[PDB]
Image 1 (spheres, helix red, strand yellow):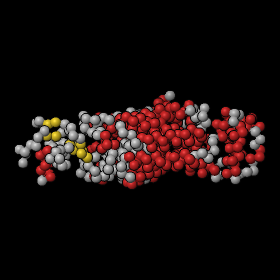
Image 2: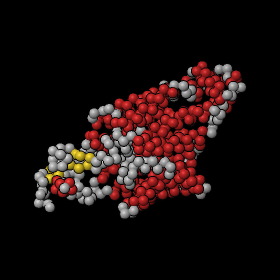
Image 3: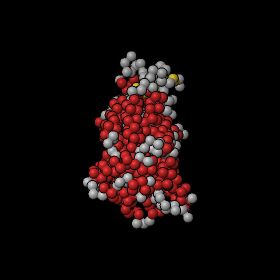
Amino acid sequence: AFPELLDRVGGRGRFQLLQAVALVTPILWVTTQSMLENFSAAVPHHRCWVPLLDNSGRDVLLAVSIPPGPDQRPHQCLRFRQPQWQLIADTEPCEDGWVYDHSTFRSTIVTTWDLVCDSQALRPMAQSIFLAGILVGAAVCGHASDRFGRRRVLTWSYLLVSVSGTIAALMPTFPLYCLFRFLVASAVAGVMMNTASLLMEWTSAQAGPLMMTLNALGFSFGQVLTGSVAYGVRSWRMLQLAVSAPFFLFFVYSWWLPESARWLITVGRLDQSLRELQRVAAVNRRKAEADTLTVEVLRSAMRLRTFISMLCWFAFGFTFFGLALDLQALGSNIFLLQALIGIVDLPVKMGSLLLLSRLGRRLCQASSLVLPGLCILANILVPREMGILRSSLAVLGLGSLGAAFTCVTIFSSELFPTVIRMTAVGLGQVAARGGAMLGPLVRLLGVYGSWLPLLVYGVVPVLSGLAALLLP
Ligand SMILES: CCc1oc2ccccc2c1C(=O)c1cc(Br)c(O)c(Br)c1
């Protein structure tokens, strides 16, 4: 009978707008802490330390000291034992440390801990560990927000994000940085599920479109907050602090938001629920029907399609979270991409949805997965002679893969007996954050050709979208 009390107490109005505003803002920084592994773990050009150069014809010394490399560059992993002055066979690996290029980044984690050359597989694992953390944090938090409430967990998760982000920026060794990022990811997943649920519960029956639109449209401007804070702070020890600092201020003000009124009824905390409903009504200024609440009323109140959705969610999660955490290979000028993956997400999603829904729901579902797969697949074909075309396709693709996140939820998830969609939307997400941990692991296949990662990242969504045409 809870919708009746909600209608008696409000619906739209004022409070349901300030709550949405105060809950949407953390989503931007939540995005910031997930795509931050693109400007923090950046790999600049690295060469081998030499006694002749870099103190104890500059080009002549560079040519005589380092053997030439395959890709029209000096070798990044080998050096001459002695100066081969015959150049107007016998080589050893770098043992005096590397020298890096300090022209766009001052200090990345790679520069600090030498994650190059033989120790290359370490870099694509710090993101898999992060996503695994997200999964294990979104699994536990489910059976946590039922014995602790729903508002307290959000505040403690804000505090945990703040503390873990601050601590992870002052570690002296790699494994501690891997572990504290794991904790950060778990807390971030908890924040994102609790915020979604809190936005869900307090709203009326019209929670379907508006709130789920606001959550996504929040992630988009998010990308543009990374782009920006980056252009500003370049180092890596001063970036994690500058990103995790706002969460403490968020926790400080999160102590006043009223707790969800539906959970309080089912556990027997009637008096606090009455107080929360009364304060919500007072905020909403609809203090006319609040008199009727005299406790007694609240006392009385107290298979093929599923598989197709699973594959669609899995394909969406795998390609995006494995080709968007490597934008240094999709082009150049990183502080422009990871900053245009957003202004090309909102017009594109709106226009594509509006145009393709009238054709049909299944046509819209199919057209949103084959298109970006083909777009990404075409990227390897075009040579590097024209940069603008080399970089244009990826933005539109990764942009349209974002369109699945919305299209496959507010237009999909009805492919079932149609009782309530909330028992299917959650089931889809387990595969997304359970295939992104199987994401950047594909980038570990840089050896044995460099085109295979892009080929896989393009073919998998293509096959998923094409098989989606086999619904009957
Ligand atoms: C543009 C689409 C999009 O952009 C992001 C940027 C940062 C974090 C999540 C997302 C995101 C998601 O839809 C999403 C949400 C959750 Br929850 C996940 O576990 C995974 Br994987 C992906």
